[PDB]
Image 1 (spheres, helix red, strand yellow):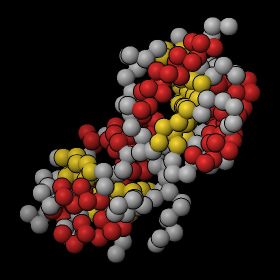
Image 2 (cartoon, rainbow over the protein chains, first blue to last red):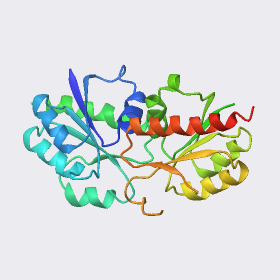
Image 3 (cartoon, rainbow over the protein chains, first blue to last red):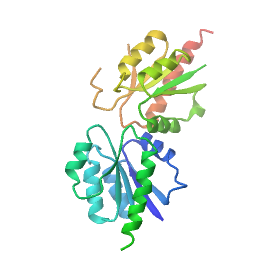
Length: 129
Length: 124
C-alpha cells in the first residue's frame, strides 16, 4: 500500500513515464500526479507519498525546494530525481546527507525501474522502526 | 501514405506524445519515430513524411538543421516545432508549440498541418 507521487511540468513526460513502468511488478497502490510543486504539496498533504519522483528544475519551484518541504513533513519519504545536463552539480550542492537518487536524461526506463525497486526497499526499511 | 515523423531524443516524450494524440480524429496512415536528426533523415529517405514534429534544440542535429534537410528533400512536408521559452528566441513560416507542451495545442497544430496536406493533396 505504497503511494508514489510523480511530479513534472510536462504531461507528455509523466504519461511516457507511467506508460513505461511496469506497476504490476512494483508494490505501489497509488500513483498521484502533479503539474508543479505548489500542486504536489497540496496533494502530498492530502495523501502522504512514500516515494516522490521529480524533475530537478521546474519554473517557480524547483524539485529541490519541493523535496525540501516534503521532507520537512514526511522524513520517511524517498526521492528520485530525473536530472539533466548539469543538474548534477546542483543536486550535490543542495542535498548533503541524504540519499541522492537520480536518473540521467535521456531517461532510460530500466534505470527508472531500479531506482523504484530500491526506493520501495528503503521505505519499507524506514517503516521498520 | 500520410505519415507523421516524430523526432525526439527521449523515449518517454515520443511515447507520451503518441499516447496523447487522438489518432482517431486525424488522417495519419503511419506514425514514425526517430531519436536524432540523422536517424530521422535516414527514415525520411525511405518513408517520405508529410508532417515533421520535432524539438528545436537537440545534440547531434538540432530541430533547425534537420528541418532544413527535410524541407530540401520534401518541399511539401509541413513541420511542427516544440520549443519552450529558452529558444523561442531563435526566430516561410513554421508552426511551434511552447513547452511545457499541452496535448491540446499539439493536437490543434496536427489538425491544421493535416488540413494543409489534404487540402493540397487534392491536386487529385
